[PDB]
Amino acid sequence: HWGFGKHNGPEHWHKDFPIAKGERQSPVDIDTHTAKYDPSLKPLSVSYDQATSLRILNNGHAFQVEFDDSQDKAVLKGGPLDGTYRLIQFHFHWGSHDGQGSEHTVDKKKYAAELHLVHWNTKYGDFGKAVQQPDGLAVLGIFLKVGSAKPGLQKVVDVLDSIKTKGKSADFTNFDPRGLLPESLDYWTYPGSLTTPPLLECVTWIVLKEPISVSSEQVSKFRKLNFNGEGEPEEPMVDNWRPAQPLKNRQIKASFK
Ligand SMILES: [Cl-]
Ligand SMILES: [Zn+2]
C-alpha cells in the first residue's frame, strides 16, 4: 500500500511501519563540518570481480539489479565493517528533475540521484535473517550528478525501455558494477536503516564523498520508467526518494579530511 504518492508517500509510512519514527532512520543530511574524521577508520574493500548479475526488475517503486549472492568473493568488507558482506542487489533513487533525487544530502545539497549497493553480513546466513540484526546489512551509497556520461551505466539505462512498467523483468547477465564506482573510496559512515519499508534499522551506511558524473540523457531515461503496471494509466516513476530523517543521537564519521 505504501508508495511515493501524496497519500501513501514517506509521510504516511509510519502508520504501517512505526519504526519510521525510530532512533536510527535513514537517509540523513551529512554536515561536513560536524562529521568527525576518524584517522583509524580503514579503507573500504570492494571486491566485485566475481559479482554475477542475474536480472533487472521494475518493482513498482524503482528498478533493481539482482546478483547471485552465492558468489562468495563478491564482497564488501573493511572500512567500518566487521566480517564480510555479500552483494545482493543495487538500485537507484531519483527526482522529477536534476535538482533533486538523492536521499542523503551533503550540507543540505540534493543530488540528481543516488545509487545503493546493498550487501548482507554472511554471519547471518542469508539476507532475510540479516535484516533482523543491527549489523545485518552494509549499503554503499553513491551520488550521481549531471555532467559527463558514465560508460559503465549505459547498459543499465539502455535496458530500462524493456522494463517500463511494474513487474517487467529482463535477463541482465554480465553486468560489472565496478563501472559505477567513482575514483575515490573516501566515505562517511553511520548506523541507519532501510529507506523503503520495512525501514528496518539494520544498516551500516557507507556513503562515498565522490559523486559519479552521469549525462543528462542517462538520468532522464530513469524518469521514463512508470510506477504502474501495463494497461493501467501512465504514472511516470520520479521522486522515489525518502527525505532526510532526524539524526537523533548518532555520529556521522568520515574516513578522510
Ligand atoms: Cl543515454
Ligand atoms: Zn535505496
Image (cartoon, grey):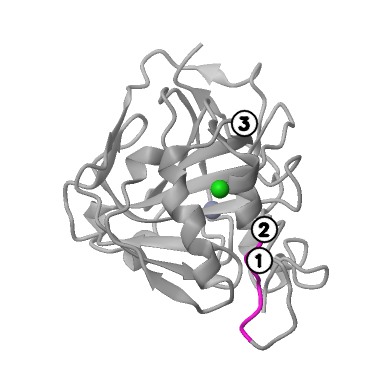
Q: CA distance from mark 3 to mark 1?
A: 39 Å
Residue on which disc 3 sits: 147
The answer for how far apart the CA atoms under marks 2 and 3 are is 17 Å
- Counting residues from the start of the chain, the first of labels 2 and 1 encountered is 1
What residue appears at the point 63 percent right and 46 percent down from the top-left corner?
217
Instruction: Tell me the kind of residue under disc 3.
Output: Gly
Which quadrant of the figure contains the N terminus? Answer: bottom right
Q: Secondary structure at mark 1?
A: helix
Q: Identify which residue is drawn at 57% across, 77% down.
A: 166
Confirm or deny contact between disc 3 and disc 1 (CB under 8 A): no
> Mark 2: which amino acid?
Arg
CA–CA distance in space, label 2 to label 1: 30 Å
**What's the magenta region?**
224-230
Horizontal placement of 132 versus 68: left or right? right
> Taking the image as drawn, is residue 63 in sight?
yes
Can residue 27 be seen here? The reply is: no
Q: Looking at this view, is 41 or 47 the one in front?
A: 47
Please identify the quarter of the rendering in which residue 251 is found. Answer: top right
- Give how far across and how far down residue 213 sits, in percent: 55, 32
